[PDB]
Image (cartoon, rainbow, N blue to C red):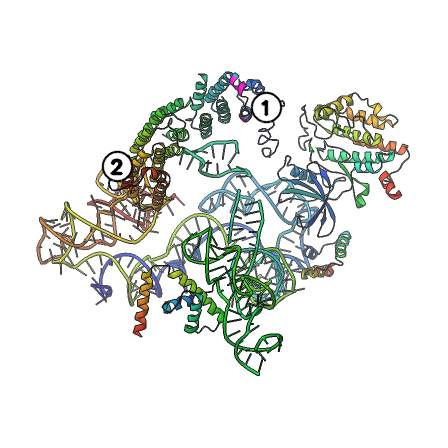
RNA sequence: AGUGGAGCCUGCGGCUUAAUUUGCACCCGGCCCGGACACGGACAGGAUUGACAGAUUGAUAGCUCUUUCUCGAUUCCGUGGGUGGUGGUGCAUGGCCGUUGUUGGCUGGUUAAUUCCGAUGAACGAGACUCUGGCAUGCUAUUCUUAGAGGGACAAGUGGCGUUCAGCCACCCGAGAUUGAGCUAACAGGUCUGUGAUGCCCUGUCCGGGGCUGCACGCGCGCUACACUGACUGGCUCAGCGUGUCCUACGCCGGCAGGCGCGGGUAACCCGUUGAACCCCAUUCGUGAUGGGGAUCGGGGAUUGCAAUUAUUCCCC
């Protein structure tokens, strides 16, 4: 839902952006292998915003 | 190891016993945050934990209610796991060597007024109000009081038709008689008026640090409760707060004379409490006696 | 101890061939297992001798008509060759 | 949720509620609740107090029961008449149960026994089963055996599905009967054996099994009566290969022969060769179960009824006269 | 003995057909839905949602055709050789089943019935795979050290427990009645929401009615006959393999199919001593497309099914 609703490409409020980047702050030192879909969500995020 | 609740919580040690269960500590194995456990046996005399779950999910959102974590059934038990909370008011009463001051009891009075406002705006009564029943927060909640133990709670008003539970006499004393009302002692149907009469009773318990009917002994439990009742009518209102401000006295007089279907003005009570608080020249700095004895160490 | 399939099979066929020349105790049975069978393994030789001894101590306790007709049948087979 | 609690009527009422006021027991509870028993027909309130009365009534207030048995008999009798006129089940069932308890613990008593007895033929199973079990508990816990035996005889002679019901009564109550009433009951039972209905035959063979299995004394059953009923039972032997009634017929004839040998051994050994010949003939049936049953029955009779008396009988030759000749015949 | 001849049925071809599905699949009508991305249009002046009533319809239906009331941004129109996603498909891939002993332990209605439905735990032990040691005053260059071979132990013997046979226990003798080494594993049966911007190929449902061989013909299976070694009527007298909660005894009514009632059978128990047909014994028939043969039709009755028309099946003329 992260990936597809970033693919909606709407006018993102910046508190929402702070919350999303705060989640990515939440992923600093975890070792568990997050999938290719994680990098797909990041790809859509850096492609849109 | 020996027992895992929820599939991701590891159980610890007992911290206390509830009205309808036992209270344990637990640690989440996924993220490490610490939770509190209410466990009850699936075959007992009072299967009321699902009603407690309903009352906790009703009371969500507002201040003074711990947020719901999980509920389930575990191989002989039903367990409802909640956010961790700190000690109750009686633990701080024991830690402070049995002495409370004016500023601290007005902080506690404002907090329990807010709690009673929240619970009667959420259409339910408590009927077991006691200093053990009101817990204290943890972390940034260290200045916020919390209300628990909906086991003896019941519905007192309807959302649609604005109707109360019909009045009927001969009701058994569900809560404790140290802070039970005269109407609760007689068997009159408990309402919000009896609730803040119990608030006044725990208030004078915090102020005087002793009760004249505390530790009374009689032939039986019913005789004890009855004797406490007629000595409660035998006790005048003003003599209970001698040497004290009359705010508590006329608060007790106001909450005593309330009717059944009336809606009390809680804004009036909060206004009077904050007027007394500012005329004794104190500020809301949250410096409690337990807090200052922590910094004194 | 248990006994394998090949021991009891070889024992049954060796009874059916040469019941006449056998004995009753472990000595005579291991002797005739030496001088009748190749049996390169001494361990399997001891096993086959023990189980044919068990077969002997089982079968002369039965009726003599079956053992008798086995004797003239084996004698007929031997005289035929 | 509230039946499984310890405080409920499941456990604690059976233990501590019987101690009424600290002493067990007082019928002042019942002496106060006549007012609910009279002029009130509210459901689930009469039934609950009847349930508690049934539960508490077993804790032996026996001299008080003997004293106010007249008051209880009249009260529960008017309850019986009113509830029979009204037609309820639960109140009637537990008032049957508590009258059964009262009659077990203790001229008018014959009337109360008749009132308890008359509700067996009541078509509701809950009423009928409770009445049957109550009558069985009263008789086995007797001067009232003649009356209930005559009632069962008249109830059979009056009548078809209730026939099996007081046949169940006869099955559960034949050992506690006097000898003449046993004879009359067996005559009526063979009278309903004149019919070809299967269920009545199987149930009354079960009644014979319960009669002879208990090993009754000489007062209940005599040796001559046993010989006569043994000779009468030879006339049916269903065909050869029915295997549901033939099993029961062999079993009851085995038990009757065992009881006859136990009463008078020489007559039993004298009557044995006919039964052994019929069993040998019945061994030609194609069913394996009847063959195993006949073998087991003859083995049981040989081990228990034939073996210990052979020192008394002695050696038998080809010219024996007494029971030795009977042994030679069944050989 | 036939088939190939004749009538009828059926199978492939072929022919007719809307279809006569094919190596309910077919036909005739009516519903329902059916990308985003890009760019250009309409949209609060209003995008769009819901709807009673009447109608079309084979029938009804805001799923359509009339007349306006309401929901309001939850939007809807067009063009792409650009992808594609509720797609199908294989590989590596992590978890999880099954797979290759022993002893315990009742409120309710309902029935003949402790009948029926309905609420309502424990322990104990666990390689039968391969090799092999203790004792040799024996053979070998040899009783004290050697290292090749040959012996010795096989549950062999005894007494109890034992399905009286598999096995168990204890014990004598014996050096040895079991002391040491090596060996968990395996999933071609798989399962389960995970991992590769993993290779590939693309971007239907329910309802009504019909047809499922309709028949000039070619090639084959079959059934009934062309009669006298036979057809008809009556009489007489004999099976077996199976199957059965639809097989059926028996009573009554009708001429028959059939109808009503009352019993048995979860079965070597009842149909059922399975009263079968050919066959046997008497009557009529007389070489006649005839009392052989029955196709195809006309009328009526009965039965199974929601429904028998294009003849479901049976009976009578």
Q: Position of residue E27 (x, y in %)?
A: 43, 56
**Mark number for residue D24?**
1
Viewed as shown, does residue D78 lie left or right of E200?
Answer: left
| Residue E12 sits above or below residue B179 on the image | below
Chain at numbered mark 2 = D
Disc 2 target residue: D321
Give the main secondary structure of the magenta stretch. Answer: helix
**Most extreme residue toward the right, as rendered?**
B281
User: Which quadrant of the figure has residue B92?
Assistant: top right
The answer to which of D42 and D200 lies nearer the viewer is D200
Q: Mark 1 Cα within 10 Å, few/some/many (few <14, many 20+)?
A: some
Placement of the C terminus of chain B among the 4 image quadrants: top right
Instruction: Give percent across and percent down for residue D258.
Output: 36, 36
Magenta span: D50-66
Mark 2 and mark 1 in contact? Answer it, CB < 8 Å: no
Magenta stretch holds residue D52 = yes
Distance Cα–Cα, label 2 vs label 1? 68 Å
Q: Which mark is residue D123?
A: none
Q: Residue at x 43, y 19 (%)?
A: D110
Where in the figure is residue C15, as x and y percent of width and height? 38, 67
Name the foreground residue: B37 vs A47.
Answer: B37
- Inspect this view and state whether residue A34 appears: yes
Residue D228 on the magenta span: no
């Amino acid at each position: 839902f992260l990936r597809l609703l970033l693919d909606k490409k709407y006018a993102l409020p910046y508190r929402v952006l702070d919350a999303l980047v705060f989640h990515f702050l939440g992923f600093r030192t975890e070792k568990r292998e997050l999938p290719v879909l994680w990098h797909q969500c990041l790809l859509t995020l850096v492609q849109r915003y | 190891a020996e027992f895992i609740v929820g599939g991701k919580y590891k159980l610890g040690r007992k911290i206390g016993s509830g009205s309808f269960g036992d209270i344990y500590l637990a640690t989440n194995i996924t993220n490490g945050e610490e939770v509190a456990v209410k466990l009850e046996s699936q075959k007992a005399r009072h299967p009321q934990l699902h009603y407690e779950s309903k009352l906790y999910k009703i009371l969500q959102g507002g201040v003074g209610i711990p947020h719901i974590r999980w509920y389930g059934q575990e191989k002989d038990y039903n367990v409802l796991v909640m956010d961790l909370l700190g000690p109750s008011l009686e633990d701080l009463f024991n830690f402070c060597s049995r002495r409370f001051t004016m500023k601290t009891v007005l902080m506690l009075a404002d907090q329990m007024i807010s709690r009673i406002e929240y619970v009667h705006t959420k259409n339910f009564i408590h009927r077991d109000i006691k200093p053990d029943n009101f817990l204290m927060g943890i972390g940034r909640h260290c200045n916020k009081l919390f209300l628990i133990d909906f086991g003896l709670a019941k519905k007192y008003r309807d959302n649609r038709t604005r109707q109360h539970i019909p009045y009927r006499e001969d009701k058994n004393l569900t809560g404790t008689a140290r802070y039970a009302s005269i109407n609760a002692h007689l068997g009159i149907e408990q309402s919000r008026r009896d609730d803040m009469e119990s608030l006044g009773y725990v208030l004078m318990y915090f102020n005087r640090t002793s009760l004249p009917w505390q530790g009374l002994k009689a032939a039986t439990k019913k005789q004890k409760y009855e004797k406490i009742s007629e000595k409660k009518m035998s006790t005048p209102v003003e003599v209970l707060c001698k040497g004290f401000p009359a705010e508590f006295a006329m608060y007790l007089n106001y909450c005593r004379g309330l009717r059944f279907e009336e809606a009390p003005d809680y804004m009036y009570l909060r206004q009077l409490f904050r007027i007394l608080f500012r005329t004794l020249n104190h500020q809301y700095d949250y410096t409690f006696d337990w807090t200052m004895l922590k910094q004194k160490a | 101890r248990v006994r394998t399939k090949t021991v009891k099979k070889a024992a049954r066929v060796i009874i059916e061939k040469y019941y006449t020349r056998l004995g009753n105790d472990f000595h005579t049975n291991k002797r005739v297992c030496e001088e009748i069978a190749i049996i390169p393994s001494k361990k399997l030789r001891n096993k086959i001798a023990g189980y044919v001894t068990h077969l002997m101590k089982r079968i002369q306790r039965g009726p003599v008509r079956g053992i008798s007709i086995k004797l003239q049948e084996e004698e007929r087979e031997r005289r035929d060759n | 949720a509230a039946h499984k609690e310890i405080c409920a009527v499941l456990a604690a009422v059976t233990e501590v509620i019987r101690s009424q006021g600290g002493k067990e027991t007082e019928t002042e509870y019942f002496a106060a609740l006549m007012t609910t028993m009279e002029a009130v027909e509210s459901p689930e309130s009469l039934a609950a107090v009847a349930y508690l009365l049934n539960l508490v009534l077993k804790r032996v207030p026996s001299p008080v029961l003997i004293k106010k048995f007249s008051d209880t008999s009249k009260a529960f009798m008017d309850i019986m008449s009113a509830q029979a006129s009204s037609g309820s089940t639960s109140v009637l069932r537990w008032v049957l149960s508590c009258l059964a308890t009262l009659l077990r613990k203790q001229p008018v008593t014959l009337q109360v026994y008749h009132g308890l007895l008359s509700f067996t033929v009541h078509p509701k199973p809950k009423i009928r089963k409770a009445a049957q079990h109550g009558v069985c508990s009263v008789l086995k816990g007797h001067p009232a055996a003649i009356s209930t035996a005559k009632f069962c005889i008249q109830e059979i002679e009056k009548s078809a599905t209730t026939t099996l019901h007081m046949l169940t009564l006869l099955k559960d109550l034949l050992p506690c009967f006097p000898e003449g009433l046993v004879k009359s009951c067996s005559e009526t039972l063979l009278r309903v054996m004149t019919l070809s209905h299967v269920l009545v035959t199987a149930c009354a063979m079960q009644a014979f099994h319960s009669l002879f299995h208990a090993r009754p004394g000489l007062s209940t059953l005599s040796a001559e009566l046993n010989a006569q009923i043994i000779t009468a039972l030879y006339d049916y032997v269903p065909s050869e290969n029915d295997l549901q009634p033939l099993l029961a017929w062999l079993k009851v004839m085995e038990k009757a022969h065992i009881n006859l040998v136990r009463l008078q051994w020489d007559l039993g050994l004298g009557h044995l060769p006919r039964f052994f010949g019929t069993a040998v003939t019945c061994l030609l049936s194609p069913h394996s179960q009847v063959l195993t049953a006949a073998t087991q029955s003859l083995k049981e009779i040989l081990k228990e009824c034939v073996a210990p008396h052979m020192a008394d009988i002695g050696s038998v030759t080809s010219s024996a006269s007494g029971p030795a000749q009977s042994v030679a015949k069944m050989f």
